[PDB]
Amino acid sequence: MQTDTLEYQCDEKPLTVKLNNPRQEVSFVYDNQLLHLKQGISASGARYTDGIYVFWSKGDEATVYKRDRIVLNNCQLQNPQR
Image (cartoon, rainbow, N blue to C red; front, side):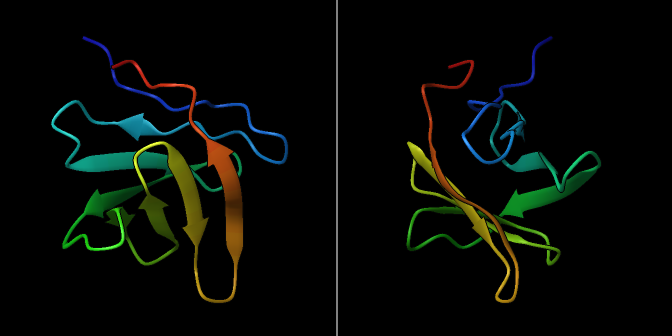
């Protein structure tokens, strides 16, 4: 049983995403606490959003922006678990 996870080590922030295997959900790190964002209607990529932040996964690029507070805007994923 393994959760998929992103690069988890970006220049600015650790992008430790808990990619749920069906990729229906991400448990994402605010800083040192985890929230849960989920993929809804994606158009610009794959959007995992909860409300706290809006996580946008382009597939290989991962950014996460609330429209007031972006926490990560430059992570380009090596590859997750898969």
